[PDB]
Amino acid sequence: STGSATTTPIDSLDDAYITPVQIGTPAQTLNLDFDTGSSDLWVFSSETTASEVDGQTIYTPSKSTTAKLLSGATWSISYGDGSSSSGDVYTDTVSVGGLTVTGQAVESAKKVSSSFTEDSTIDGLLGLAFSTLNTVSPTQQKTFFDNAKASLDSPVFTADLGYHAPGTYNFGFIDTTAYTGSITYTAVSTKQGFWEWTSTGYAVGSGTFKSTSIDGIADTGTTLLYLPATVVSAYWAQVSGAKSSSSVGGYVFPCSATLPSFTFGVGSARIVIPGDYIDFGPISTGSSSCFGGIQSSAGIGINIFGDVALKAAFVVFNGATTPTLGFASK
């Protein structure tokens, strides 16, 4: 089997991407944030505290003939941005892009934090990291990918995120029309439950490439590129008037600037992030200070190749017995 679904930016900045997902029978279509940095499939639901729902589409298990309470199971998750959610669990049929899993754990939110409530465009998350991170207790549950894997033509999924445009998530096949040149594969460590890999270095603009190992995660659920402070300082030093602002919470730059590109290494290959991808616009409406898309990881504990980086590539998440990542230009 295979599946193929279009993923769409939620706003003009590409702050996140949503992908329609069919849950239940008859289908209830929710728009979920596919997150390769977490491992829970959770939804706004008929159980979510009413004051915490503001425009999201909800899953109502009582209207699904295939929903079953997963008795005794609960979940609770906290993300890197300080957001959180928790609730109980159903199993139900879940389809993405024509690929169906029966008996998928669908984590129904009873509580969500304010950042979720305030984002009317995101109806929940679909985690695509390793199932070792799934938060369901007392019986940990599998991700949609892990449940689909054995049925897929190839045990892979791919992320092809657009810059200010829709893109695609494919399951079970690699669309050889979707990228240019060849795919470079690199090793993955699953020790922390992430798609964790080591970049071979970076360049700023037309500058020389610096060979240096940067361990980090491929995380579709993170907007920005978070790298070591040395790397980030070297990038922003090439932008007149850029500075780190403790009041704003990262590097800002004059909206009048033209940003340089940023290159990262994948083995001997190179992915170039155009400068425009690094512009996240005014810090507040009408400001002439703009927020940067490359930020320091120093206060996180891990480097994160988020959407800024991943949208410059065609990315293969190879879930074979020994997982690997692949990157191609496009």
Image (cartoon, grey):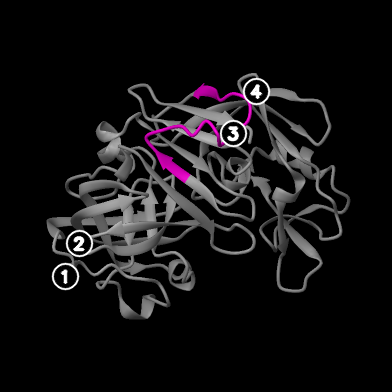
Query: Disc 1 versus disc 3: distance between alpha carbons?
Result: 43 Å
Q: Which mark is residue 25?
A: 2
Q: Mark 3: which amino acid? A: Tyr
Residue 196, horizontal then vertical, whole percent: 48, 32
Q: Is residue 78 left or right of residue 217?
A: left
Q: Are marks 3 and 4 in contact (CB under 8 Å)?
A: no
Q: Regarding mark 4 in the picture, which secondary structure is present there?
A: strand
Upstream in sequence: badge 1 or badge 4: 1
Instruction: Look at mark 4 in the image and give the residue it sits on.
Output: 269
**Residue designated by label 3:** 179
Can residue 230 be seen here?
Answer: no
The residue range painted magenta reads 169-186
In the picture as drawn, the residue positioned furthest to the front comes out as: 177
Amino acid tagged 2: Thr
Q: Secondary structure at mark 2?
A: loop
Distance of label 2 from label 3 (alpha carbons) = 36 Å
- Disc on the earlier residue, 2 or 3: 2
Q: Where does the image place residue 227, in percent across and percent down from the top left?
A: 63, 39
* Within-10-Å neighbours for mark 3: few <14, some 14–19, many 20+: some
Which mark is first along the chain, 1 or 2?
2
Q: Which numbered disc flags the more N-terminal residue, 3 or 4?
A: 3
Q: Are marks 2 and 3 in contact (CB under 8 Å)?
A: no
Q: Main secondary structure of the magenta part?
A: loop
Q: Give the mark, 4 or 2, whose residue is nearer the N terminus.
A: 2
Q: Which residue is mark 1?
A: 62
> Relative to residue 222, is residue 181 depicted above or below?
above
Residue 150, disc: none
Which residue is pictured at 58% across the width and 58% down the height?
Answer: 15
Relative to the observer, which residue lies in front, 296 or 171?
171
